[PDB]
Amino acid sequence: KVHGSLARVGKVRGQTLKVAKQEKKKKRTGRAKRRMQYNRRFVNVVPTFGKKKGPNANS
Amino acid sequence: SGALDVLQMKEEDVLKFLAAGTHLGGTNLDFQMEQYIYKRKSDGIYIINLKRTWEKLLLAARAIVAIENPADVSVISSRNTGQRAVLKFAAATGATPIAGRFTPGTFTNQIQAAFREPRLLVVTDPRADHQPLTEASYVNLPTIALCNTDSPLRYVDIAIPCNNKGAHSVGLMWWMLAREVLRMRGTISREHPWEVMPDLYFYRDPEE
Amino acid sequence: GKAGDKEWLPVTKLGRLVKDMKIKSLEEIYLFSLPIKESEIIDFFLGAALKDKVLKIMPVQKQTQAGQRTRFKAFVAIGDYNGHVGLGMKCSKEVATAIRGAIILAKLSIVPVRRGYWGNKIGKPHTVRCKVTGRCGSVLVRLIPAPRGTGIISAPVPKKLLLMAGIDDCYTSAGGCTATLGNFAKATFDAISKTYSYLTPDLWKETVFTKSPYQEFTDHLVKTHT
Amino acid sequence: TKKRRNNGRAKKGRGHVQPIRCTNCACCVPKDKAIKKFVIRNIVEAAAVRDISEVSVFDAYVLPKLYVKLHYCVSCAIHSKVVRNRSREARKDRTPPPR
Amino acid sequence: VRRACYGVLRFIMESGAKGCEVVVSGKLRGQRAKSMKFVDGLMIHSGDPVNYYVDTA
Amino acid sequence: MQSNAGEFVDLYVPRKCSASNRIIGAKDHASIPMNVAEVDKVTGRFNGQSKTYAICGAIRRMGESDDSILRLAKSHGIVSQN
Amino acid sequence: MGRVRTKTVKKAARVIIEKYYTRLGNDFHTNKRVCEEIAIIPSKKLRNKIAGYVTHLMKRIQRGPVRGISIKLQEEERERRDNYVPEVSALDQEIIEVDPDTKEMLKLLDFGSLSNLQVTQPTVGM
Amino acid sequence: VRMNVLADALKSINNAEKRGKRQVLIRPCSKVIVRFLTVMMKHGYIGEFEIIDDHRAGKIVVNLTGRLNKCGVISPRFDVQLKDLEKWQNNLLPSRQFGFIVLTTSAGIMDHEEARRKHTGGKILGFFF
Amino acid sequence: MGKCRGLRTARKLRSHRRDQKWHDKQYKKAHLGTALKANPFGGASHAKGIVLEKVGVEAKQPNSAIRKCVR
RNA sequence: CAGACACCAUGGUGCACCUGACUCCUGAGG
RNA sequence: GAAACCAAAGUCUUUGGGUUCCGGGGGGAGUAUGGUUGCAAAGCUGAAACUUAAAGGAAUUGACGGAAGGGCACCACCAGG
RNA sequence: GGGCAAGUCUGGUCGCAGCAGCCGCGGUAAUUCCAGCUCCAAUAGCGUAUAUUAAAGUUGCUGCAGUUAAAAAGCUCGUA
């Protein structure tokens, strides 16, 4: 409405803490990474296994 | 055409026509039947032109001919007066007969308790056989029909002027049709008229 | 595992002629302008290179006497990439059933779409010969031919239909309601079919008409009935 | 949209009309946008008449009728079932119940 | 759910049945309950012959 | 529908009409012709060789067709009592 | 009031009547036994309702064919009876009064006949 | 009353053609109507016409054919300098392979193909295809 | 449709379109300069100010939260 | 048709939910 | 034509006979303000801030009516216990 | 989460903190939050605010709508 009183702030962040996995490997740079996506998806393992499936899907 | 003198009519027909009360028509003005009319009787009623009735009947008959199986022309009447009429036609010519109720869907309906395969429909009044007339134009079938001056002309290809309601009018036209198709292709042959009388057709006529 | 099957049941002259191979293509049937009431005819002449795209799976409903009721309405489009396409709508109790029926309906309705050129005349048709418009519910889609290498410039739903149609190059403008998708596909379907309905001066030259396959094959098609 | 084509009875080819009144509800309503009802009825009805015909002497005369031209307004005419609700298809007919 | 139901339903019908029905009831998708009927053929619920003619599990 | 000097584009060539000069398109309903048998004349008895007229959806729904067929048939012959 | 016949009874009755016409009587008791011979009916109450309706039908039937049901032999008999000849067609009817325009129809077909003239009290038929 | 005469004639033919009707009575009859009909006739879009002569203004009976799909009128007329002809032709005709835009040029009422060769523009009357 | 289209009617079309343009809400607010006068953006894109006070705002339904704004 | 025709106000809420691939697999033989 | 409807609300993407008038989401509002006409009551011209993703039309299906024709039951009434 | 490309994620919270152009999430088994992990898109660039343009036939010259959705002056004469 209009009100005036702040109450609670950063409540969720006050009990969630971050952590890190570091690296086995670097996250790839430019041209090499762009090429890598096309090879990893298609020329491998030429696709014949599975269907209707995402790159991060649990379906 | 055919052998040719009796296909320009003859007195025998003109007597049968007058007797059966073909000649009288409706009192509704026309725009599609108008050409056919000979002259108008005083204070309404149209006198159909027997010359026109002939030519159309022959063109109709000819279309049934050039089919080597006469079964795939469905003769249709739902009128009482023409139930006996079509039954005799089917015996004679070899038509597949539909007397009494049509029962909707026999040229339509994949799942049905009856199906008929025609190629040409002959109708006795398309305002009583309206169900076949509508059904036929959903499945690409030509329809000849016996039409007066107040019958629908939509989805009718070839009309035959005639009263074609009640009495001996419906009977006689079935008799003359059967006679005509048998001339070209039958066993009357040589374009000369039938030895069967029109009285075998007509209505039942209440039996004493 | 699972495997399909096929069976032929004729109730009409046309089914018998197709299986006997006195008709070798749908084009003959289309020319004579006779209905197709058997899916098997389309399957027999083609049955390969037929892609079925479900355009939407959207549910609708009506209120029953006690609480709600709901059902699935499916739109399926079918077509080869050689100038033949169909559209079929079916509504059934479940999603799967609605699509299954829709496919059968889509096949049955298959219609030729004429393919022409922008201005060219050599190297085989890439578009349409005439601009064709179709309306559905106040949506109007206008297809305009486009030259080679332009590609299909259309919204996703009409573009898919055009692709199957064999129109690889097209300009479109659609006006009206854009929220409605069943209408949009239907209007494009009206437009593509209209190409045959246009009379071009290249199509003026006249013909002596069919004597009907029913009449000519009459004797052949006595099997137990004509 | 129009729920009655003639609006309860038309007034076309006429630019205005005078109002009539109701004969039992007295309320102003147009004359040809309201129900008009002829009432022809015997003077001695179906009631009185049975003893009036037997008791009469020196008489030979067929019974008089009372003639009154009633006018009803819409709200009263629906209510007491002079007219009553009907199908929307049936509305397109000008054909009324026979007398 | 639908794949499992269709396969079993189709197999039981194929064996020879006048008809059959499979119902899956309970919760799905969190906190709402649902039922589905996957039916084929003829089924009755009429009088005493139901007990005789139909086997249930 | 030709392209170039007379290359064939096209899926098929449709039927035409002469009762209104309008094509029968593409799978349409109420589109059928009408084979009238010829008779050889003089000795009677049907000999071939059909006269065919093409009837379109349009004419039939506008209730023209009856008159049209007669005009078409008469103009090219032949029926007795013309 | 209650226990009006159901479809199951009537269908069976039509069946039986057509194909066993000569065997069937008009008496409940004998017909009940005939229904055991010519059919398998899994209840006596059902068989009784069938048998019962079949007697009622036979009674109506033996006055000629009746509504909603026909027997093949009776259909043949009616067919043969109707050979009826009500004209022979023209009577002859030659040279009688005809309408003045029907007259010109005969006239220009090389006949003519006597014909009606004059109009008095139109509208005609009124 | 009539502020264009082309527009009435063109509609009249099209409405006849829809029916299958093979006659019209167009009027008031003018020089431009005659000229438009002849060019139209030559390409086969309509059949032959016959001008009946009266001292009113004349009346023409056109026997038409269904080889036409639409004869439109560009009312009010616009100037065309042979570099708006191209714009019109893509816009309002279904292809560049057929159909004519018919204009009036100082070298006569002519189809736009002939106009292009002459390189004489003028005022656009209408089109057909 | 409903417009004039003679051979001299340029002036009438030119002015009629201009007159009707003003009706539209999106057009009018911007062209009358209303947007600048009422709201501080329109004629600027970013703007810096001094904080007057910190406000808690007990957000109007739907959605139950304290939104929390500054003035 | 052509007997009688009366006061009566107020009141709240959520989850209806979306994909195709026939085995009890027979399991002496196979 | 979205339909209801409609021989015009037809001859509109195949878009164009002539001319005129009015509208540009819904509310604020025919309100504010200035002018004008009126003796008066009133009439005409006619804003904004702000508010908000629905306001609205039509048809469809349900539910409900102290709207109209109906039926059926001692969980309803009747006659009564 | 949808439009929208890519989580029927794992922990944490539980109509709280926040998210949210818009539609809407979060009231305990949150695929919208807060972190982590994974994946996507563009890639030495990318996000954001704002003016304007396109899409928009939502200003309709080309090319609008006005029976009922926003919209024919009460009606006629009549000069520009």
Image (cartoon, coloured by chain):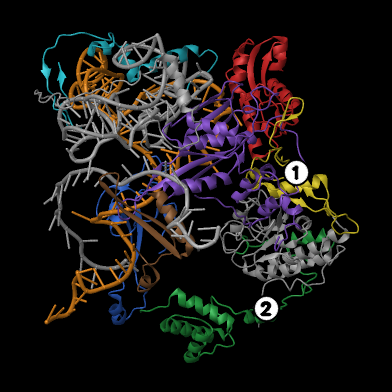
Chain colours: C purple, D blue, E brown, F yellow, G green, H red, I cyan, K orange
Point out the image quarter for the C terminus of chain H: top right
The residue pinned by badge 1 equals C209
Amino acid type assigned to the residue bearing label 1 in the image: Phe
The N terminus of chain H lies in quadrant: top right
Reply above or below: G115 against B158.
Answer: below
* Residue D10 visible within the image: no
Residue drawn at the location 73% of the way across and 60% of the way down: C222
Q: CA distance from mark 2 to mark 1?
A: 45 Å
> Does residue C153 appear in the picture of this structure?
yes
Residue C117, x across and y down, in percent: 65, 25
Is E36 on the left-hand or right-hand side of B38? left
Check disc 1 and report its element: helix, strand or loop. Answer: loop
Pointers 2 and 1 within a single chain = no
Task: Give the residue pinned by disc 2.
Answer: G79
Position in image of residue C46 (x %, y %) = 63, 43
Q: Is residue A32 left or right of residue B95?
A: left
Callout 2: helix, strand or loop?
A: helix
Out of B136 and C64, give the one closest to the viewer: C64
User: Outermost residue, right direction?
Assistant: F43
Q: H127 or H57: nearer the eye?
A: H127
Camera-side residue of D39 and H44: H44
Hey, which quadrant is residue B176 in on the image? bottom right
